[PDB]
Image (cartoon, coloured by chain):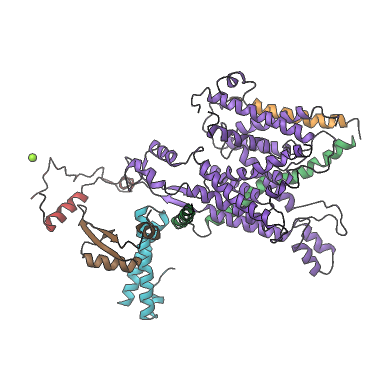
Amino acid sequence: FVEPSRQFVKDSIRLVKRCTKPDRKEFQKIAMATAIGFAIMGFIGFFVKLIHIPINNIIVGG
Amino acid sequence: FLEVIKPFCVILPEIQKPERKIQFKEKVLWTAITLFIFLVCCQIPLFGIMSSDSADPFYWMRVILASNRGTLMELGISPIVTSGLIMQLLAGAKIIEVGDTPKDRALFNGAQKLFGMIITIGQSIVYVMSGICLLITIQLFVAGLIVLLLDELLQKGYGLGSGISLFIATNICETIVWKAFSPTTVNTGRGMEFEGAIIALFHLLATRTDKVRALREAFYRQNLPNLMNLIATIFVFAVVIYFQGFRVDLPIKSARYRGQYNTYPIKLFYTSNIPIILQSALVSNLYVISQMLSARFPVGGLCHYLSPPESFGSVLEDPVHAVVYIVFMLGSCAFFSKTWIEVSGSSAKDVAKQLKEQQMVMRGHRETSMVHELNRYIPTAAAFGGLCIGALSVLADFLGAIGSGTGILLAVTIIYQYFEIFVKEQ
Amino acid sequence: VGPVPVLVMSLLFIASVFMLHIWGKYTRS
Amino acid sequence: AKIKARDLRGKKKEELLKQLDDLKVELSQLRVAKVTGGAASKLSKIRVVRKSIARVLTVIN
Amino acid sequence: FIVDVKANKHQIKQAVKKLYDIDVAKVNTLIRPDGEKKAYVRLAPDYDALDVANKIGII
Amino acid sequence: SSHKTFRIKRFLAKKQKQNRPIPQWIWMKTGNKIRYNSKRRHWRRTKLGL
Ligand SMILES: [Mg+2]
């Protein structure tokens, strides 16, 4: 009942070495490019900031 | 079970994609219009019952969708997410039966829509519950049906990431971004209008003297967002893209062509666990939905095996909650890998029949030994690929550098797959 | 979506919300 | 690095042989990557390692 | 393994012992019609061939 | 024959590796005149010598 634990823990250390896992250029590319992609979805919150609270003032005031 | 309800329930379907098949950039137009909608969709509701707590599953729930007691989003995409997940469960788990004719499968999508919209109505009713109960229900379904149509017009339509996952991603960009520039603060004992922005920690240098205690409030800010929090948030992003590039290469002699080597990879993400994290999230969202039925017949005793322990103090007052939370996170993502891969593709037979189906044969041995060529990676790179995400989200909670934990890890995982989808068409 | 009205339909729904939100708020202040 | 011969000539016999062994192990691993099926970058790196080995053995001779 | 054609079983045994730090029960050699010599290097059973194959990369 | 020498076997080994077609990138070069390997030996037609 104890040995499948041994199996998976040795099984992990198998496929860690088979992977590539390179340096930073990949890391660099998805890093900067996808923080950029984040902020593409990001400033949208600053525009519901700029809009939907002042029009909620329009809502409650009238 | 399928043969009766599905033929009757066909009410108001969606229109399948036209004959304008190949295009580059009007694809992106159909994306961007939905992104205009979720500019708009996160906007204020019309009913004035101003309840005190915003949502009860507001944090985990917020991580999935953050319009808690808010807009037409709606405290979460938790309707569409939970209703999608248990649907794919009860399709994959054979409690309910496979349809591969283009019809029963069409009405299977119809019943998918049915249970999805009914669950939206259920969430609407259960969050709004006085005598002002009219028309909330009408609003919610209208705004449930809209998210339905926008998601299914971004699977058979444009769809590259999904409708779903890129909604989660962009709303997570926003939830970092409100923490990025933060205009208001209700005034505490000192210091109005500066809450965890970098502008806040640049206006703070303009107001106060004694810049040492201007540094201290900038880097060890607790109740509002922090800039040490933002360093840890950036740090997590860097590490997770360090781990996306973990991939296994397998070169392939194509059949019938001399020596082209388009090596099939297997990244450790194993679909980036958009099942498996949301597997970890939505069960702990459905009870914190249904603790509301525990008030009558709870946020206390049921919480000790329900949630993270939320404390930056690693030796906070209960190790039971910490141990069980982390072990459940790791085991949940690993287990839902080893159960997930069998349904949404890329299991052993899946890969084999796709490669035979696209005429790609491993060099080392015969074509249907390719299974045994690669059956010794995919489950572990499911399971470990499950496991060391959730423990990774442990490091998203154990240390507070995330504009948010688990959910931020996984919405940027959405983005990372998203980049691949966009790049695909180059 | 053989047709694009479903989207347009969603836009109409938001407008109905958009306009009808401030429409009752017209008489209030 | 770019193993140039001019900054191999001042160095000693022992460091030339250790650098030779480092490059021989490096070429062995690139041939493993050629036979298992690896990147294109390793497959173009194999010529860099072969010519660097030729350079080091040349300077030794 | 694929081996240079000028090699003995003794030389293949010493090379496998030195490059990968593993002891060998026996070596069987054949020369292919391609021209290469192939060596089937049996290991002493305290070593796993799958572990040393995962060490050197082949899987 | 099933009984060979090393010399004859190495001779046959070379002719078995010369017997492949041309790679399909070789005719995308600048000054190509080569459409196919015109030295292809088949074992029934041409008997290789010896
Ligand atoms: Mg004859």
Q: Identify which residue, E38 or B125, lies in the foreground.
A: B125
Residue B207 figure quarter: bottom right
**Which chain is assigned purple?**
B
| Quadrant location, the N terminus of chain B | top right
Q: Is residue B22 above or below residue B369?
A: above
Residue B420 lies, in percent from the top left, at 54, 45
Number of numbered discs visible in the structure rendering: 0
**Which chain is assigned brown?**
E
Give me the residue at 60% from left, 35% from top.
B86
Residue F28 figure quarter: top left
Question: Left or right: where does residue D4 sit relative to residue E17?
Answer: right
Q: Is residue D26 above or below residue B150?
A: below
Q: Is residue B320 visible?
A: yes
Q: Colour of chain F?
A: red
Q: Is residue A42 visible?
A: no
Question: Left or right: where does residue E50 sit relative to residue B396?
Answer: left
Residue B48 lies, in percent from the top left, at 85, 35
Residue B88 lies, in percent from the top left, at 57, 34
Question: Left or right: where does residue B157 sit relative to residue F8?
Answer: right
Of the four image quadrants, the one with ligand 1 is top left
Question: Left or right: where does residue B320 sit relative to residue B357?
Answer: right
Q: Colour of chain D?
A: cyan
Farthest residue, direction front: A1
**Which chain is assigned orange?**
C
Give me the residue at 61% from left, 55% from top.
B237
Q: Colour of chain A?
A: green
Residue A12 lies, in percent from the top left, at 48, 55
